[PDB]
Length: 6
Image 1 (cartoon, helix red, strand yellow):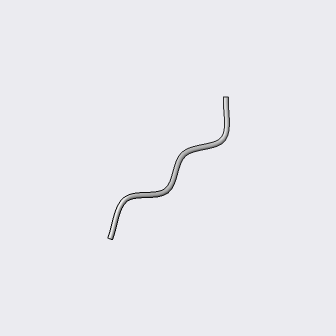
Image 2 (cartoon, rainbow, N blue to C red):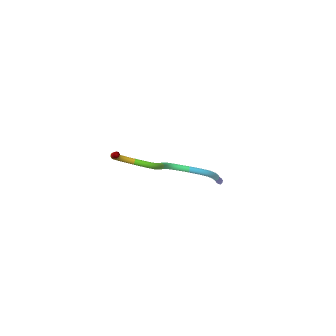
């Protein structure tokens, strides 16, 4: 699981 908000 990978989640990113930039």
